Length: 134
Image (tube, rainbow, N blue to C red; front, side, top):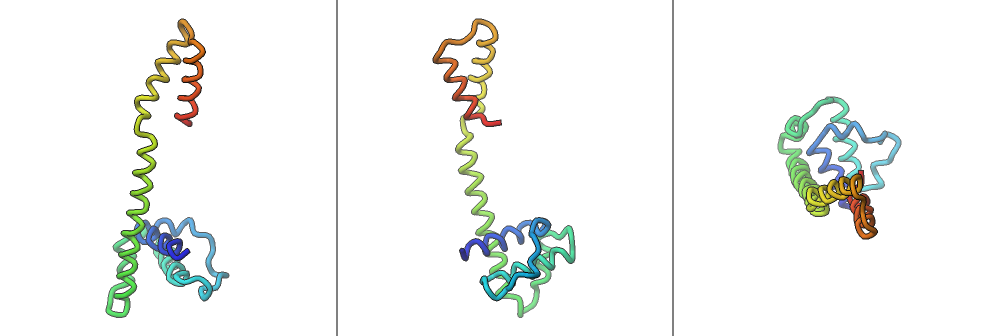
């Protein structure tokens, strides 16, 4: 639950164009979920300057007064980039052999259109069709 806010903050700092996908936060009350005030603040800053880059966003956090905040904004950016690199990795792992599966599939289809397929081969084609979900 604490990482939810941190992930949101982090992702938005990494890509401020995501402010675009935040529904309205005005009627919420800040006082109820730690970090929400910060999120709201960034979202507002993002809406007030569309097209922002990460660096341009981080300009609003110069000065001594903002240092503890600038800090967490950068930490959280990194924690988030890792979380999604992790997720890309796990997702790529799952599709590792796709190039190889998707040509046994071509081979089975071609076999099927000229000679046809045995019972086992029909089942394998079916399995490949599930696995290549598009």
